[PDB]
């Protein structure tokens, strides 16, 4: 079972002996720190951490003893605040005397603003605020996945509007293929759920149960898939029988959309000769509600997409839409699911535009690029102490390293406000108390072991909409 | 609770319908496919087998749950209820799968078979690749353990050159990655993988994983020491950094203590606060209880070099038997910012050029060690190589025209020692010809049971550097 006493960086076990004597309050905050592009971030994922790990009776006698035994060996010394943990057990029935205030989930906030704050509610527990730094900072991951996914949605929206004149099907155009390419089952669920803030297409099944348990949707499920081959289901037929595999699969899934990986041996042969000649009769007969989606999976991603489109354009009837861009017949589409990240997505859609192909033609799948190839320094997600009370006097505290101004932190008690022009500002030094800027946008979401405010997944999605969608 | 019926890529739910009719066997394998990182450490499959795959993993409730989810997720009924029910009824929900694998901790060149998977019941031909997704997650502990070992090789080379021995090597790269990984589960897995090569960690999650799944003769596989963070210095107020330092080193007067020194001005902290104001509290410390000064910002090489130059003028420096400068035994440095395999190399080489022994320094690495890694670094990949259809075995493979690097292996596979003592993978069942001795793979899972396993002590032994051996 999970033990919050064993869920911190080891060194934090020793910090209760390091703060100034007579310290009754430690107050800390989280930001995606500005760096001298990702100019705005989607705040998502804290509610998962609050419910799974921080709420309710999280301290027991057994958990205290267990931690004491492990730390004895791990440090080869007796440092461990057994008394401090016993106090929370006896006084609060093991509930954390902590208050957390946060911006609503789904909110889209510029870099360098306070996103949440943490402080102890009992003077004895001044050490507890930063004990939970480690677990709370892991919110960097769903924030960053949700943010990077939204930035990809912006690119897709721009090019789809330009080449087609609308945004139809935008939420279905970037699929999560990342389940195998993340570091753990838990990561898979968190990451998949963060992608679903922006899109509806996923093969990372783990995201669904996470959303149902911790957030919830009006709809039965937040994400959807369609039948699709993998190389095993083609190659099992034997090298000389690729056409047999294709024919069998499209006939098995004749009335729903079906994706067929087409590059096992020669993607260009498969498109021109197998799909384009031998099996053409099984393709042109398909419903608009049940297209074949041809899937290349190797080679230079842009060069391969353009060549596949070129081949299919010469084998199938192409129209020109009202913006002047070429469109495949409605029973045929393409999905590129190899080597797609934010950079290559941009290259591909711009390449398509230059060659006059509508973005209606194509969907994208992304795996490692979407869920694994991200770190905490992409958005500089960071947790810092900004205010303490010592001997009953508050002091505004901060770091400001001489050789790196980008690592300077904020001072004092913080609040988040709308500006007169409708943007965001973080007020420092308790200046929100002067009430010159309307209401603080941070709300209490956790207090003394209870989750005090929750958001549904539908609300989060609404908060995270693109401006272009709003327009 | 975990449900293996809901722990695969969505599209695999539809694959049972796509294989050739009358297929009784699907046989697949995992490799770190060949195209830096010429050899890989095999680690982490034992965790997956025990946590997720062994015993009764199918129940009536789990089947109904998956049926209900997939009905909405596909907007159609495509889920193989009958196939899963067969497993429940016939095998009391134990997976009729056999997995063979190289021993954990083994160091194997790229492009070799590391494990294989096949069904043991013809009805369950579709099951082999259902579990691809979970098994392929082994890329992560493999990659962490591998990249961590590559860093140990660098540290070994430079420590040996500047000091003449390897004393303390295993304590020189510390895992600081707990906050920087994507989940609690990842933290434990990744920390355990670093502990294959090193003994220093602040990612507490790794300890419990190892104890549960691998085991060590020692009470714990990894260790930490007291250390400050910016909040324990800055809480004292900007004019009282010296007061913070004095309090901390006095509280931890008889054990090693690390104290982050860059809150305001690292160079002032080293030269004036440690080097003058509090110098008397440093030179009095035991060899068993050094102060470790921790810079945490600026260019990593430049900052380390300047910190060492400052301390070298404030404290008595010696010259070791190799001609390199050495701080007194009560004083060391740790660089825990910006460290990855590339910057590690730059820092130790830069120290060597300035005649500073690698004894003087330890490193901590967080996102670089545990997060900034992907499955394409070692090209970890699972593919089908052999099937039986209508009673006839067929060697199968992919070989995409535009990427010969993606070509997969054909047929039944085995791993062998060559006459020169290296590894070779034989394809097409050629291992059966017996020209290359016994298969080095071992059966590790069969029909719901883990059949062979390794302690963490054995894994560490297998993963040793040549220089250590
Ligand atoms: O290729 C794979 C998965 C590969 C995979 C998975 C996991 C790991 N590694 C690889 N999945 C196929 C998904 C693409 C389906 C498209 C999306 C857009 N689209 C519609 O929105 C639609 C239009 C008209 C009618 C109905 C729907 C047409 C159907
Ligand atoms: O700075 C932090 C943690 C920072 C942190 C943690 C988590 C997240 N973010 C930042 N930890 C201090 C590590 C100090 C390691 C050295 C290794 C070599 N060494 C001995 O081998 C030794 C010498 C004499 C006696 C006993 C042992 C001296 C101690």
Image (tube, coloured by chain):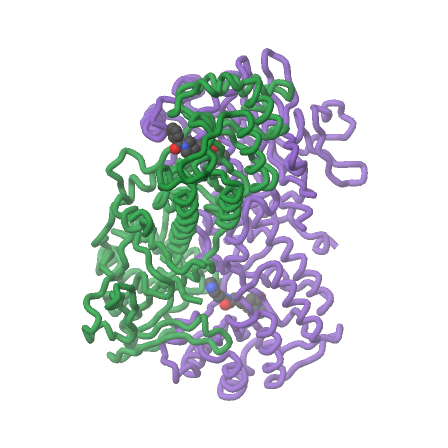
Chain colours: A purple, B green
Is residue B251 at all visible to an observer of this figure? yes
Q: Residue at x 52, y 88 (%)?
A: A277
Residue at the extreme right:
A420
Residue A237: x and y in percent read 36, 79
The relative height of residue B346 versus residue A330 in the rendered view (above or below) is above
Q: Is residue B410 left or right of residue A222?
A: left
**Taking the image as drawn, is residue A8 in sight?**
no
Provide residue A53's location: percent of width, then percent of height: 45, 35
Occupied quadrant, residue B394: bottom left
The residue positioned farthest toward the bottom in the image shown? A277
Where residue A170 appears, x then y in whole percent? 63, 61
Quadrant including the N terminus of chain A = top left
Q: Nearer the viewer, residue A352 or B34?
A: B34
> Along the horizontal axis of the image, is B219 left or right of A353?
left
Q: Residue at x 30, y 51 (%)?
A: B105
* Quadrant of res A22: top right
Judge by depth and name the residue closer to the eye, B236 or A318: B236
Residue placed at 27% from the left, 78% from the top? B393
> How many numbered dots are placed on residues in this image?
0
In screen coordinates, is B150 left or right of A315?
left
């Amino acid at each position: 079972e999970f033990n919050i006493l064993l869920a911190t960086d080891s060194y934090k076990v020793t910090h209760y002996k390091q703060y100034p004597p007579n310290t009754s309050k430690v107050y800390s905050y989280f930001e995606c720190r500005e760096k001298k592009k990702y100019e705005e971030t989607v705040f998502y994922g804290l509610q998962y951490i609050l419910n799974k790990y921080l709420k309710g009776k999280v301290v027991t006698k057994e958990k205290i003893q267990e931690a004491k035994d492990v730390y004895k060996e791990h440090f080869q010394d007796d440092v461990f605040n057994e008394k401090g943990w016993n106090y929370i057990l006896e006084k609060y029935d093991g509930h954390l005397p902590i208050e957390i205030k946060a911006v609503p989930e789904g909110f889209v906030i510029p870099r360098g603003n306070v996103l949440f704050t943490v402080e102890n509610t009992d003077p004895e527990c001044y050490w507890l605020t930063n004990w939970i730094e480690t677990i709370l900072v892991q919110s960097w991951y769903p924030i960053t996945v949700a943010t990077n996914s939204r930035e990809q949605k912006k690119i897709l929206a721009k090019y789809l509007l330009e080449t087609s004149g609308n945004l139809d099907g935008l939420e279905y155009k970037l699929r999560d293929f990342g389940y195998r390419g993340v570091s753990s089952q838990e990561t898979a669920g968190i990451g998949a759920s963060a992608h679903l803030v922006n899109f509806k297409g996923t093969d990372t099944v783990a995201g669904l149960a996470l959303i149902k348990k911790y957030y919830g949707t009006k709809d039965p499920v937040p994400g959807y898939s369609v039948p699709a081959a993998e190389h095993s289901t083609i190659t099992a037929w034997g090298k000389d029988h690729e056409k047999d595999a294709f024919e069998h699969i499209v006939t098995q899934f004749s009335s729903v959309p079906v994706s067929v990986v087409s590059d096992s041996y020669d993607i260009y042969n498969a498109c021109e000769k197998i799909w384009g000649e031998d099996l053409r009769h099984l393709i042109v007969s398909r419903s608009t509600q049940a297209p074949l989606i041809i899937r290349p999976d190797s080679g230079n991603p842009l060069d391969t997409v353009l060549k596949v489109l070129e081949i299919l354009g010469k084998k199938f009837p192409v129209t020109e839409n009202s913006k002047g861009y070429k469109l495949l017949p409605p029973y045929l589409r393409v999905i590129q699911g190899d080597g797609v990240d934010i950079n290559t997505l941009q290259e591909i859609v711009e390449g398509m535009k230059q060659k006059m192909w509508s973005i209606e033609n194509i969907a994208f799948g992304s795996g490692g690029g979407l869920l694994q190839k991200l770190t905490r320094d992409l958005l500089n997600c960071s947790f810092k102490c900004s205010y303490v009370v010592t001997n009953g006097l508050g002091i505004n505290v901060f770091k400001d390293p001489v050789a790196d101004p980008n690592k300077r932190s904020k001072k004092g008690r913080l609040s988040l406000h709308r500006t007169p022009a409708g943007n965001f500002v973080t007020l420092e030094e308790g200046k929100g108390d002067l009430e010159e800027y309307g209401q603080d946008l941070l709300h209490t979401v956790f207090k003394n072991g209870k989750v005090t405010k929750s958001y549904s997944f539908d609300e989060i999605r609404k908060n995270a909409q693109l401006n272009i969608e709003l327009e």
